[PDB]
């Protein structure tokens, strides 16, 4: 099926990681308690990845090997690509303030939508579940 509401189940080094997005303390004092999700809904070989948080709902559409903008609610810019291979996604992003890459990655296992993030270094993981 892989077309669903998902929502955050767990997260790990998620504040460590946000600290190292060069977010700032008080973002985190709510990231603490903001949570994160998807409404994912693939279509003809494409991905409507409606990704969202207490910060703000983001529509992140892509069709396969496509580049685009993404922006935090605080006031940050970030752009990235996505593509689909072996029923799992491989994505990548980059600040344009720092000037660094971030390396996201999505996958649907266990009727559960894992994600994982890498900021210059720092592997976070986040795991989601259906709804």
Image (tube, rainbow, N blue to C red):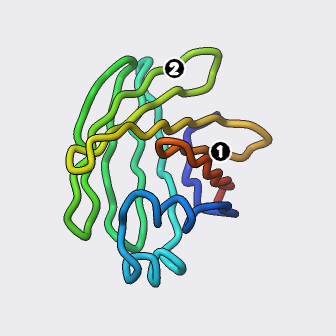
Residue depicted at 41% across the width and 24% down the height: 46
Closer-to-camera residue (53/99):
99
Judging depth in this view, the residue of 49 and 74 nearest the camera is 74
Above or below residue 75? Residue 78 is: above
Callout 2 secondary element: strand
The image shows residue 115, relative to residue 35, as above or below, that is: above
Sequence-wise, the earlier of marks 2 and 1 is 2
Residue 83 location in percent, x, y? 45, 21
**Quadrant including the C terminus:** bottom right
The residue singled out by tag 1 in the image is: 113
The answer to whether 103 appears left or right of 114 in the picture is left
The residue positioned 55% from the left and 53% from the top of the image is: 5
**Residue designated by label 2:** 84
Look at 48% across and 43% down and name the residue there: 40
Is 122 in front, or is 63?
122
> Where 8 sits versus 101, above or below?
below
User: Is 6 positioned to the left or the right of 41 in the image?
Assistant: right
Q: Residue at position x 26%, y 41% from top? A: 99
User: Where on the picture, by quarter, is residue 80?
Assistant: top left
């Amino acid at each position: 099926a892989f077309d669903s509401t998902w929502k955050v189940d767990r997260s790990e080094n998620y504040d460590k990681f946000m600290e190292k997005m060069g977010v700032n303390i008080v973002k985190r004092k709510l990231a603490a308690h903001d949570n994160l999700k998807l409404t994912i809904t693939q279509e003809g070989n494409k991905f409507t990845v409606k990704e969202s948080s207490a910060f703000r709902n983001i529509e992140v559409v892509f069709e396969l090997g496509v580049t685009f903008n993404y922006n935090l609610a605080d006031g940050t810019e970030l752009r990235g690509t996505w593509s689909l291979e072996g029923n799992k996604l491989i994505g990548k992003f980059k600040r344009t303030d720092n000037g660094n890459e971030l390396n996201t990655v999505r996958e649907i296992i266990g009727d559960e939508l894992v994600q994982t993030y890498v900021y210059e270094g720092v592997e976070a993981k986040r795991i989601f579940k259906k709804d």
